[PDB]
Every structure is written in structure tokens, then in C-alpha cells.
Image 1 (cartoon, rainbow, N blue to C red):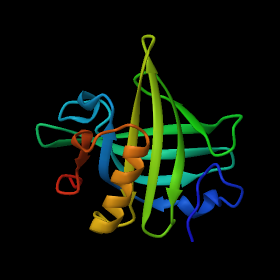
Image 2 (image 1 turned 120 degrees about the vertical axis):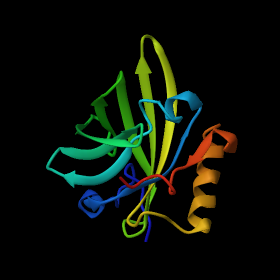
Image 3 (image 1 turned 60 degrees about the vertical axis):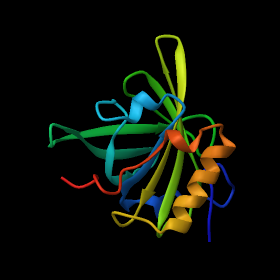
Length: 157
């Protein structure tokens, strides 16, 4: 079964655990390109009472650096906020818990904004059919495929 974090049947405990960044997408492509601050490789999600602890690593000159963030529940069910290179809010429009997790994030920095979408997998890659479903979700949010970057061949340290 599939769910959305904003849906009535969402079970947040089921997204706990191992995840990997498979694809990132954005309407400001520079944010997820090689030296972008949002080209983050997720490692795990730790579900707590009213927050999610997110563990990531970044890459620079073939060198991995760890980073943890705490995302807090907001007043809207299924939405979380976190401070990182500006103010971010995100939701999980679609997940099947056991294979994939699709997230939609809004960043706000210096009075501007951009959208980021991420496809995360329980393993270090996902099927091409799930990747296509993600491209369709990106299209529904006005993000062109040329702004979708598959990072499955670069998500391990």
C-alpha cells in the first residue's frame, strides 16, 4: 500500500530506517549540481515523537562529510520544517514504505524560494518504473526532466 504524509492513513513510523538518495530534482538546478548545498545523500531517517532526525553526507573532491538535521512537525499534519541554508518545509507526497519515498520541499532563503523533490530508496537504487513515477510527480510540480538528476551512481562513499 502507498501513502502520503498528509493523508489520514499515513504511518510515520514506517519510514524509519535506512534510505538512500536516488534522484534529486529542483526548479533551481544549481542547488543540486556538484557543489550545490542540496546535493545531499540521505543515509537514514530516525522517527521520533514529533520530529525526524535525518542523517546525510555531502561530497566534495571525492570526500564525504556527515551531517545531521532535525526536522520538526509543523501545524499541518505530514509537514516538517528544518533550518538548513534557509528555512525549509517538506512533505512526503508518496511512499510505499518498503521501497521508495518521494519528498517535496520548499526552501526559502534571502527572500527567495525554490522547490526540491527527492526520490529515496531502501536500497541504493530503484527500478526504472519507480524512477518514471517520480519524473511524473516532478512534472506535476512544474519541474522539467532536465532538472532531475539521477545520483544512483554516486550515492556511496
